[PDB]
Image: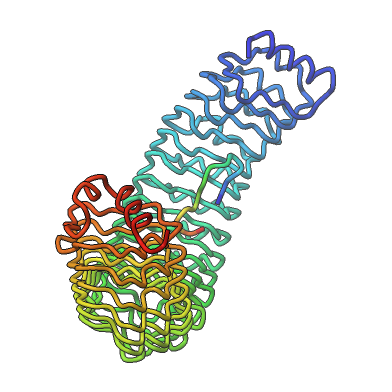
Amino acid sequence: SSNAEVIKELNKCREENSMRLDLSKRSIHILPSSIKELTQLTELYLYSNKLQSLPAEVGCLVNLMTLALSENSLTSLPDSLDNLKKLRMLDLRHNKLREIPSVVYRLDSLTTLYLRFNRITTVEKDIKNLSKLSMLSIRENKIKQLPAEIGELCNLITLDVAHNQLEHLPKEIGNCTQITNLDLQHNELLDLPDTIGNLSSLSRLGLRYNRLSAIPRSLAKCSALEELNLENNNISTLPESLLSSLVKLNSLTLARNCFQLYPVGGPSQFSTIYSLNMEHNRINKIPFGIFSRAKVLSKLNMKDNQLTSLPLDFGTWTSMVELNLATNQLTKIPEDVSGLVSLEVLILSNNLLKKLPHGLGNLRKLRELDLEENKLESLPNEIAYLKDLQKLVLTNNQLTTLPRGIGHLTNLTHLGLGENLLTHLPEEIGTLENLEELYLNDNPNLHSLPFELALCSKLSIMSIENCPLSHLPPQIVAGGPSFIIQFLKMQGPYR
Amino acid sequence: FKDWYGEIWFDGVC
């Protein structure tokens, strides 16, 4: 927009006595001082422009309740904004602030303040003057400390300080008894204040990517917690039965910490959670009976730990829908796996399995089975009953042949057999109606392909690189999968 | 969650 077009918009706003002025997304460099005549405005939108300064005449808009300055190049604000005694929402995200503008601390009518993605380094004590703040966002700045005066914001409900450099929280934070959403992800927190337990309305606590080595015992008093994310810290234990007290917990993440065991407390601590993430720790066992009360537990991730076997009652996890045990030291899957009738995803990558239990074929709803990077020397005939299976990953195992029953996997679309010892594929491969991707690359003993492979009418991706295939015409295999399938098709019994 | 500006916040606990 040119200066004249902006003035035309102001004049239209005046003539129509409009209470809303939207000048966003116009590449405006200068806001003309003529804005002073629009005293009836309650909402002024100027986001996504090129403003490097705001005219002091904006202070004449005494009726303003919303001022959005997002995505400009502002470094300051005129002191005349003192006169906006009714301002409720101020958005200064995506500017060039090295500080909270001095005048903002005097806008004590504010209930919503967005400072996200600037270069602010300090939160002055004067923050106490904004006692009506219910939503405060200082996400993605350079703040290294919060003043104790933050505890005077007793109406604070949502506080987002994600992506800063905080090492501690002032204990006075416990005076914000209304806080229900607290995001502290990606800071440098060494600990949490014991007063944190005062936040009895806290429902979401984001703490991923910090430096916590322990959780305060008083966190058990935040009984409204539904989402607790402790990913990537330095925690090895949880205080006595902390989880048992979180009666609304829906999902818990302990991944990327220092746990050698499950937190002590028994099955009472998992009675409500829907998903449990413990990947990338050093847990050496799943306790017997810890899920006996986990009636809604649907997703368990134990990837990259120290499991050498599964618990005796493994077969009782009838509500489990997604289970990840990759990168452990499992040498066998118990036959009791047949009890996981709700399991749809099973990840067993990078273990020490040489064979699979017969009970695997009872997982009637299993859709994804990842077995790459094991030592599998064969597949059980029971796999024929995995009728819901869509993806089967067997990359880098020791398979030489496939069970003929594999032809009953009519829902299978992805079959990854790369880096195996296959000598041939069963003729029943032709009944894989929905097969789309067949990876056979790096099978140095695979000298043939069955003509029935031409019957897979949805096959569009196949890799045979580094497969001998010496039983097929050399010029055929030299042409790649397109000529190979063509040969099997028009040279076979099914043309 | 998506804030009024359309940006996401509280990712990790939403």
Say above or below: A283 vs A150.
below
Return the x and y of residue A6 as percentages of the image width and height. 68, 14
Residue A100 appears left or right of A443? right
Residue in the image at 39% along x and 58% along y: A207
The image quarter containing residue A412 is bottom left
Return the x and y of residue A73 as percentages of the image width and height. 49, 23
How many labels, in total? 0
Along the line of sight, the residue nearer the viewer: A433 or A352: A433
Return the x and y of residue A182 as percentages of the image width and height. 49, 56
Residue A480 appears left or right of A13? left
Residue in the image at 18% along x and 71% along y: A398
Say above or below: A495 vs A263.
above
Residue in the image at 73% along x and 28% along y: A62
Along the line of sight, the residue nearer the viewer: A225 or A199: A225
Can you name the residue that lies furthest to the top here?
Answer: A4
Return the x and y of residue A106 as percentages of the image width and height. 58, 35
Say above or below: A344 vs A179.
below
- Coloration of the structure image: rainbow
User: Quick check: can you spot residue A218?
Assistant: no
Residue A327 appears left or right of A133? left
User: Quick check: can you spot residue A259?
Assistant: yes
The image quarter containing residue A435 is bottom left
